[PDB]
Amino acid sequence: TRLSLAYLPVKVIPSQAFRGLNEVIKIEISQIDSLERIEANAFDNLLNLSEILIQNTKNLRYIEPGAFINLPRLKYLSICNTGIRKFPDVTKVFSSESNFILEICDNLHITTIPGNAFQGMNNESVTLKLYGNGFEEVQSHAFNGTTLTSLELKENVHLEKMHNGAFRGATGPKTLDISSTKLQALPSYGLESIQRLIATSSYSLKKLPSRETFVNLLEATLTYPIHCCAFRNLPGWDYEYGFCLPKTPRCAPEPDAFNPCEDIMGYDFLRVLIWLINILAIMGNMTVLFVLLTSRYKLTVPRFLMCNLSFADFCMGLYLLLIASVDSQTKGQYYNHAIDWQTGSGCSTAGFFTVFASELSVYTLTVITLERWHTITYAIHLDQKLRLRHAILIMLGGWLFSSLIAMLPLVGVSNYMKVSICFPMDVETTLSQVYILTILILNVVAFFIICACYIKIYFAVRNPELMATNKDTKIAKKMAILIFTDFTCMAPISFFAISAAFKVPLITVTNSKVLLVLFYPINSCANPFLYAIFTKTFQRDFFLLLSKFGCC
Amino acid sequence: CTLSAEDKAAVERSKMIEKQLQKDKQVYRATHRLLLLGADNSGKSTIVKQMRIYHVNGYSEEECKQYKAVVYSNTIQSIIAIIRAMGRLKIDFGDSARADDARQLFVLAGAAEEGFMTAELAGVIKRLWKDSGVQACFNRSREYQLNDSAAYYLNDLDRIAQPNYIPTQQDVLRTRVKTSGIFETKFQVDKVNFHMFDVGAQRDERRKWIQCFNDVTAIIFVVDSSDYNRLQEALNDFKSIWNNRWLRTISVILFLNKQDLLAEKVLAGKSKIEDYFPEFARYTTPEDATPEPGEDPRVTRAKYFIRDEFLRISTASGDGRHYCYPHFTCSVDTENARRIFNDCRDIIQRMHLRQYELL
Amino acid sequence: ELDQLRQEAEQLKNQIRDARKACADATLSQITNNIDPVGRIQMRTRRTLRGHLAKIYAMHWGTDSRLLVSASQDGKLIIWDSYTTNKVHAIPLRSSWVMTCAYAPSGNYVACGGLDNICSIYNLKTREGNVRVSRELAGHTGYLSCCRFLDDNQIVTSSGDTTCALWDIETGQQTTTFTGHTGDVMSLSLAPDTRLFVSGACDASAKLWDVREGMCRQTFTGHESDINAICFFPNGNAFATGSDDATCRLFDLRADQELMTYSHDNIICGITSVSFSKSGRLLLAGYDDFNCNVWDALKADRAGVLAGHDNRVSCLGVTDDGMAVATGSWDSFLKIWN
Amino acid sequence: TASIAQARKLVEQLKMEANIDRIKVSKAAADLMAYCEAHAKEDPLLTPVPASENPFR
Amino acid sequence: KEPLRPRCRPINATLAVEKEGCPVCITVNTTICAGYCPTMTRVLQGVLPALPQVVCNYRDVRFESIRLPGCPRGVNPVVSYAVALSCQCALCRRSTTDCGGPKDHPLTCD
Amino acid sequence: QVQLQESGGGLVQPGGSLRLSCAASGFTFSNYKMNWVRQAPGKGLEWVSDISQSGASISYTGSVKGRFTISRDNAKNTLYLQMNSLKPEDTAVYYCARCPAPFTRDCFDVTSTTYAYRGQGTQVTVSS
Amino acid sequence: QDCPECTLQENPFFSQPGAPILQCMGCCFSRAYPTPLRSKKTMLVQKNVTSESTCCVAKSYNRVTVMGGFKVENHTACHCSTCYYHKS
Ligand SMILES: *[C@@H]1O[C@H](CO)[C@@H](O)[C@H](O)[C@H]1NC(C)=O
Ligand SMILES: *[C@@H]1O[C@H](CO)[C@@H](O)[C@H](O)[C@H]1NC(C)=O
Ligand SMILES: *[C@@H]1O[C@H](CO)[C@@H](O)[C@H](O)[C@H]1NC(C)=O
Ligand SMILES: *[C@@H]1O[C@H](CO)[C@@H](O)[C@H](O)[C@H]1NC(C)=O
Ligand SMILES: *[C@@H]1O[C@H](CO)[C@@H](O)[C@H](O)[C@H]1NC(C)=O
């Protein structure tokens, strides 16, 4: 009633050779190097047979078309760890057993699954356990003519691409496992049949199809957590409803606190506001550079440093342009794009600007404000005044420092990929924590010396015994603006970000978009006012450039 | 690029000259040029003597070289003025010996060098000036064009005539002072150098040479506290300096000098300020005052009234851009160099704050 | 008593005035309706002599048209090649406060002076590559407001002490004096007949002198305020005059009177320097407005402007061949317009 | 007071300035017109020239 | 363990072992995972998924080894082999196991 | 060209009152700030009073505040000085002095000896 | 530890009162051992461990309906036999 064919010199299975048998229910053809091929109609109408296990036969190089044919009772058909170079013609078995279970596995030689490859093989429903084979592609309508219940393409590490209409001939799948596949994307069609996905590992699957495609979906398992927030959108034991309870599509794993799911701008007001701030911080810092570079007069140190400040603050405009660009590109639809953006060099680039722009800006503000204190402290020793060579030396130090600190994330000391807005929000290692603590602590210290500078100025400048109190107070009522804007930029950011750098997060990362767009740009948009456009020596150059452009 | 040897040599001259100029640029920027003014009764001379006490020693080897060329130029100009006078005079004043009339030619030839005074010239002019008939010609020519202190240079010549000699600075200053038009009464505080420029031996009209001093870091307006009646003329002089288009940008220090002389005048009770200024009857010592111990309040009221009159003029116009800084002093005050320095610092600081827009 | 002398002076002055009015049969602006106005003059800063150190107060071209002297109250007299912008010499000064400088007509010597009343002369044909004072032509009682060389042995000097004086350089004893002004005397100009030199009073007047005659032939007076600068029309027959009254004015010697005013009601700034192009057809003026204005000397058109300075124009000069126009501002920048 | 001599000198200078000749302005103008017309062909500021002619190019 | 259907656990074994080039078969007294563990199947199908059929499988192992008794040179002298330290009723890892019906394969040296 | 003539001086009694006036010619008078400056016996050229181009801004030497008053007419090209409560020491040559240059606040040199833009003066004697 | 032999038992979900639904369930043998070289020589993808195993196949059944109108298959004999869902 069963054949345990193994460890024997069989090299061909002849056509219909088994007939004469009709007591057999199960066959294995296993542990047999001798076997080269199986002839056509070998398993022809062995009607009593229900189970086949072609197995462990590296020399089984060739199975003829129709080798399995006209066999109404065939149920389980395993074809595993074999020399088979072309997908076996199972179509002609024309079985009808209640649940057919094809199990093609470990056939590293099989190039592809043909179109209609599953046609007819069972008119009753079918399942396709396809583990670990060599498939490069699934052709159009490869699934045809069947109610395909469960498809398990898992571990077909070569299957880079299903054809977008591979399901177009079949009904189903009801279940689809594509784990470890390196599949780029699911087909365009039929997926609406799927009651549950599985797609663990499968890092190539960076973009699921549209959430409304998965109308049937009851579960997924997806190694890119953000995708579960497609399924956050909503319309052993058993569930009696079947498809009648789609109201809770389960998903796993859930996103970590670094990726609470959102549109990259969590709210339309930020989406609007960042467009406003982009225009402001772009036009502001760009004109300041344009004027201060092109005007006829030679570069005084404060003019040269003011250029660097508006360059850093222009990079801030470029960064927030990207974020508003990425937001606009991905409006409502981040998850489909998210990993491609957030892991690509794209998000790593925006990350680099955030640190570089921050550090060049805040460094420049200390250099300007150390210069202002210096040239007012050592004012009368007029040979001590900071000459432009030393300013280019120090400012170049600023560029090298600020680019270096922005480069350490690229050397992996903290992944820019860790968060949607591409901040360096990663502190897995103590080194990464100390790195993030360093830049943030420096930005706190930078503010304190900016304040401490202007205090020493005010005590040095104020008239001890000849007071012109109207103007003596005008200093503080003016100079306080230069601190207060730097405070409302730096101090909010560091208060939260230092706490997060202690791994004590005090804010939801979708709320942290508010800190980004309200306060992070403040320096990079107030600075071109306070340090340039409100200065008479700039306004001269602006009016002269209007004159050079005839705009009287 | 391509050049001939002629262009290259001139370019190397240009770069050599540039490097020299760039060295002088450091000295220029390091000096706070500081115009001094004041009606001559205001004792501005006595103020520059209180600067000269800080200028105790010859400035540097490079300044000493600059005055060596001046000592030699006045040595040459005083002896050649005599050599042409002893040709122009009706007396046939060819010397007692023909060798001095021959050495006179090699003086006129040897003076033409753009280099140091060689020992030959010194050897000649001492042997000339030993003839007492040349001292008599110096008294015959006593009202012709001659350097009046020539008898110092031609007697000190004995000590001049050898390498690495140094004169004491009053001989140098005396050599330079003539109908001069300015005096550069140099001094320095805390290694900050002031080329203070006095204006003197210069005509009664200001409105053209003032347009030179438009870049001085400050103007010291010294004024006489005590010579009221005259004071009202200085108040108009200050009002003119202040409003003048080309001084709009430059801050004015005031020294109210001769405070003690005013105080004794006020202690004498003549109080003519009441006549010259009826406002004194209304004005009273402000609580801004911080008087010395033992001042008669009238003395405070006088000095502060006068000071507030200058400040009134300072306040009425342009004070949005340039300050003025009053100080009370007498010629004895050693602190004047420090008073000048503090408000010179303030004037520079309160200028930077205009362009850093902190004001 | 002066009254009879003041009535005699008044009568003489009235006769002179009235005779001028009789000779004023027409203005220049009448007859020059025959003349096509100049095309509106365009020029660019085809050099800037960047390397000066403080504010340039005066300049003068060498007769070779190539070199020019410039002097600044940093105390450097700097000699530039206009072609290469080489600083062919940079001469330190016995005190910083220059107000004027001049180039000997040979190019052999240069002169300067200022609030230190001392004139000095320098020899550029040094034996040894070091330039030093050839003579210190001192003796004035006020600041030396403007110098010009007549010859390498003769120099005329203005002063704040009202005196113009000519020095024989070798003698150095104030060899003629021309005392007839009131107030300062601002500026001098020499005709190609170097016998004749005009000097601008710091009163309203200008006087023409002859070097040998030792007194003023004429006294032109059309100006309202101080004459800041003066220059012969190139044939010597006429001379321009700038003033703190903001007007330019052209005087002709033989007319003894103003031939043409140049002004706009827009232009309240005093003129600070003047000179003519080689044809005389362009009269160039610097202002307290940093823009130079160029005037059609015949039409009184403001035929052009030279804007390219960022502070008062202190001095101006046109080369002997009219090729280019130096302008020394109170920036350190001397710009060679052409 | 020397003002007496100052006035007498002024009178003498005014006497000279009365004695001098004067010429019709129209004739002076015709000279000025002729002189400009005598030189406008060459005047480099009135009449520009190529960079081979002008060393300031 | 129970005399009837002892639940899945590591048991003693006497396992034949070799290395590819060996002319000779070696054997070691060792342990292997064997026994019984729960299995079932689902009466209702198609509307519900498949039901995973866990099997007795290696939960963890160590290794043991010996230097080979004259197998070819160039091959490493030592043969090394696992020892079943604990076992569990779990799914067979397709990547790593072959799992199916009984072979009755001789685990002696034939 | 530029020509000035003071008028209305002479003897007047102490405590008396008198108007001086000056006619200015050969220049655009409205462009200039104007001064009265006096030379009493022994004194130098004291500045007495000034009047702006507008005629609005005015000031006086402190001994003359309120006692005298100054005014100008920019059409008639002329300057007036009302004088009242005359002290004997007010005896002087009074001169009309222009400030040197137009549109100015500046007014240097009007007190300088030998200055140009100052008239011939009118004598005023305050005596009985 | 307990290990019941596989047998027909009442399905709790679908055993209609008066019409029980029988399900093959129970505990069955397996023998898992390091893959012997003789077998390895036969394999294309080589294995390091091998499991001989059995699973309770419903070797006979009948299709039957229940409330909801789908058709259940009523197991009728049980046999621990070929595993179908053991690989993962
Ligand atoms: C499938 O085939 C079998 C045997 O031919 C038949 O009993 C059954 O009805 C068929 N079902 C369909 C849906 O064709
Ligand atoms: C799928 O099968 C049907 C018949 O079952 C056939 O008509 C059709 O052509 C097949 N699809 C393709 C793409 O050949
Ligand atoms: C396995 O065999 C060893 C000796 O061959 C014996 O000591 C041990 O008890 C056996 N295993 C068990 C679980 O008893
Ligand atoms: C088989 O290989 C895997 C991975 O190398 C290992 O974890 C496992 O323990 C191995 N099994 C045996 C029995 O050595
Ligand atoms: C299922 O099978 C058992 C035994 O054959 C039987 O007792 C039971 O009634 C069957 N169920 C139905 C619904 O027929």
Image (tube, rainbow, N blue to C red):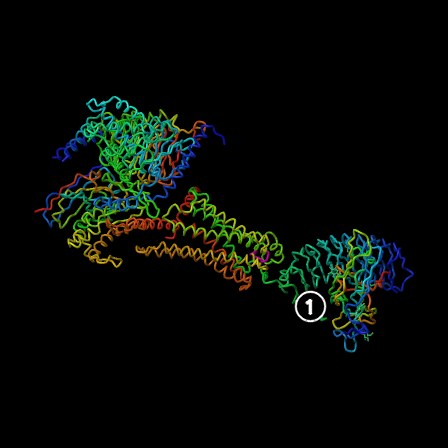
Q: Is residue G28 above or below residue B260?
A: below
> Of A107 and B150, which appears nearest the observer?
B150
In front: G23, or B344? B344
Q: Main secondary structure of the magenta part?
A: loop
Regarding residue A98, the answer to whether it shows in the image is: no
Q: Quadrant of residue G30?
A: bottom right
Q: Quadrant of the N terminus of chain A?
A: bottom right
Q: Which residue is mark 1?
A: A244
Query: How would you rate the neighbour count of disc 1 (Cα within 10 Å): few for under 14, some for 14-19, many for 20 or more?
Result: few
Name the outermost residue toward the right. A20
Tell me if residue B76 can be seen. yes
Q: Position of residue F24 (x, y in %)?
A: 21, 40
Where does residue A467 sit, x and y in percent of width and height? 31, 55
Q: Nearer the viewer, residue C235 or A392?
A: A392
Chain to which the residue tagged by mark 1 belongs:
A
- Residue A145 vertical position relative to residue G5 in the rendered view, above or below: above
Helix, strand or loop status at disc 1: helix
- Quarter of the image where one finds residue A388: top left
Residue C214: x and y, percent? Answer: 22, 27
Q: Image check: B47 left or right of C51?
A: left
Q: Ligand 4 shows up in which quadrant of the image? A: bottom right
Magenta highlight range: A417-423
Q: Quadrant of the C terminus of chain A?
A: top left
Residue B26 is one of the magenta-drawn residues: no
Residue type highlighted by circle 1: Cys
Residue C165's spot in the image, x, y percent? 25, 30
Res B118 quadrant in image: top left
Image position of B182 with respect to C34: above or below: below
F122 horizontally vs C65: left or right = left
